[PDB]
Amino acid sequence: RSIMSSLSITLNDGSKIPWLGFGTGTALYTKDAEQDVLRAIANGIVHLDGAQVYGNEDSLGAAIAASGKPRQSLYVTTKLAAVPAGQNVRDTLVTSLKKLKLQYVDLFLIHTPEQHQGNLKSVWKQVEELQKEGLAKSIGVSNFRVQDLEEILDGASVVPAVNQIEYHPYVFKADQPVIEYMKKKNIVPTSYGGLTPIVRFKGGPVDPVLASIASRVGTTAGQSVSEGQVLQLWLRAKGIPAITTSSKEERIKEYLATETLPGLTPAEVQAIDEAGSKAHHRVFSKFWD
Image (cartoon, rainbow, N blue to C red; front, side):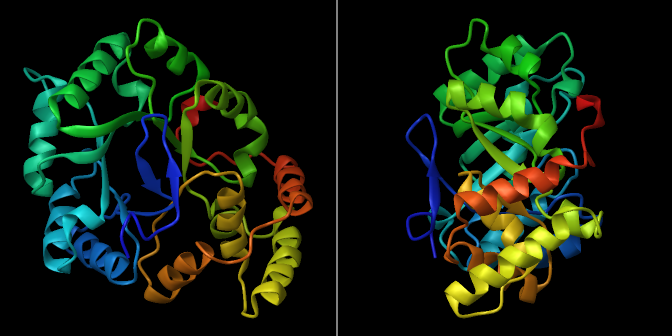
């Protein structure tokens, strides 16, 4: 499996980002983070999502090196945290690249606008220069509201390629404005937290809908399909890359299956939209509310 051999989404700069990703997330121990990345790579996930702030870039780089998979087969994202005192954005990326043991990242994101209040335009210009310098192939943002995007786009030479956000049926209704804005600017959303409805809020209104659709998709595919896999197919139907976090090979194998399971129909996506819209559950980036 490689970026080329995998389902991918085309970004506004021409590059392809694999639809299925795996993130080290907020993994507490770097020893676990490394093993989970190795498991993700071994099972065929070719999109790896890291972040400065949680300190797991060393594990991500060690796992890439230990996997035996060519780095050029993989798409690597990392994310700008706060700029340490006496440094600039470039400094953090050079530090990230040394930890990742890479010459460039495929994608460099501003992790959150809350860490750059009053300096958003300055930070984005610096990230634009890092793309010119060859250190980040594509550049984007994370957890940016419409207003935040408006700010950095005012006088920008590069439109962010992605906005990585919490995205699942229980934020669907609240996120409709930013989703519409991004589609007008050709910013691709990428989702984290895609399993939130059933991991954190099992028993809400989306569950019977997911159960019904999983039965349908399963009969079309000739294999058992879980409610979690339908939540990813919902993202796939919208063209939104899914960043996952499960450590377990059995769940990782399920994620992989959703790359090629039969797609959801319009009525099925609509039904999930509607059921999700009966409840708002935002787990991360509460400043959005």
